[PDB]
């Protein structure tokens, strides 16, 4: 293997606080008292609605990803019962900015050691993520950007995983053939099936929870990582063949 590509969710990073709590905490500070559960439901609905009409951050239909997220936050609060856009606007701006701050995130235990160990083996690393343009700066603020040759977001690529074009663009940037590249992430469709459709290897991080039936029934156990601790061992069984 020569290249390992990564998504960041439940592999490298997770949000420190649930969204409802985060939105509610911010709102309280700014004089709006909204229940976290109301915001979590509002957000679910707002995010889905926005994606319905403006897929991949609206970039193909006249929006910027910052505007897309402002729209989602405004609508989250609206559904939660705060319709005054003047009142929410500043809250939305702080949430948008805070998203990039390292204190928003927890780097998973052992993730950075795993990246360092991959590099010491001579692997090139890169990111392939359905994330907006803020991902680069998130990684930089956490001291993780240094490990990666590039960070290819769906915003930058113009197509999200599992579309073959995002993987093909990563391979072009890496100057690598698919057979020497492996992708690692936590979503069956986006991170397991997607890369394999262009001939890359892929490994699915599933956590300690019992398996999704489709994964259980359809994915070889050799490709299933309960945690990142299992990645290098999985790669060695691949190489050993």
Image: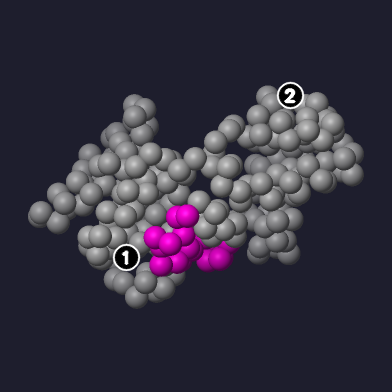
Q: Which quadrant would residue 26 be assigned to in this image?
A: top right
**Residue name at image x 72 percent, y 30 percent:** 24
Q: From the top left corner, tell me how far across and down residue 165 is, in percent.
A: 46, 66
Q: From the top left corner, tell me how far across and down residue 76 is, in percent.
A: 74, 37
Residue 36 appears left or right of 31:
left
Dots 1 and 2: beta carbons under 8 Å?
A: no
Q: In this figure, which residue is indicated by the disc labeled 2?
A: 35
Whole-number angstrom distance, CA of label 1 to CA of label 2: 45 Å
Lower sequence index among marks 1 and 2? 2
Residue 235 appears left or right of 164:
left
Q: From the top left corner, tell me how far across and down residue 91 is, in percent.
A: 78, 42
> Where, quadrant-wise, is the N terminus in this rendering?
bottom left
Residue lying furthest left: 241
Q: Which mark is residue 62?
A: none
**Residue name at image x 34 percent, y 53 percent:** 115
Residue 3 vs residue 115, the one in the foreground: 115
Q: From the top left corner, tell me how far across and down residue 205 is, in percent.
A: 35, 41
Q: Is residue 71 shown above or below 37? A: below
The verdict on residue 159 being magenta is yes
Q: In this figure, which residue is indicated by the disc labeled 1?
A: 124
Residue 238 in view (yes/no)? yes
Residue 80 appears left or right of 225:
right
**Residue name at image x 29 percent, y 60 percent:** 119
* SS for callout 1: strand
Which residues make up the magenta segment? 143-165
């Amino acid at each position: 293997m020569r290249l390992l590509t990564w998504d960041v969710k439940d592999t490298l990073l997770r949000l420190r606080h649930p969204l409802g709590e985060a939105y509610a905490t911010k709102a309280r500070a700014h004089g709006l008292e909204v229940e976290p559960s109301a915001l979590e439901q509002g957000f679910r609905q707002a995010y889905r609605a926005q994606s319905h009409s403006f897929p991949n951050y609206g970039l193909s239909h006249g929006l910027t990803s910052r505007q897309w997220w402002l729209d989602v936050v405004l609508q989250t609060f609206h559904l939660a019962g705060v319709q005054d856009a003047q009142a929410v606007a500043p809250i939305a701006e702080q949430l948008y900015k805070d998203f990039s701050h390292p204190c928003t995130w927890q780097v998973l235990d052992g993730a950075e050691d795993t990246l360092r160990e991959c590099r010491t083996r001579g692997l090139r690393l890169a990111v392939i993520s359905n994330f907006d343009r803020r991902l680069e700066g998130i990684l930089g603020g956490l001291g993780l950007r240094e490990h990666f040759d590039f960070v290819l977001t769906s915003e930058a690529a113009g197509w999200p995983k599992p579309d073959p074009r995002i993987f093909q663009e990563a391979l072009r940037l890496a100057h690598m053939e698919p057979v020497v590249a492996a992708h690692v992430g936590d979503n069956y469709l986006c991170d397991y099936q997607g890369p394999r459709a262009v001939g890359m290897h892929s490994f699915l991080v599933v956590g300690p929870q019992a398996l999704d039936p489709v994964v259980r029934d359809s994915v070889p156990k050799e490709h299933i990582l309960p945690s990142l601790a299992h990645l290098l061992p999985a790669l060695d069984c691949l190489e050993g063949s």
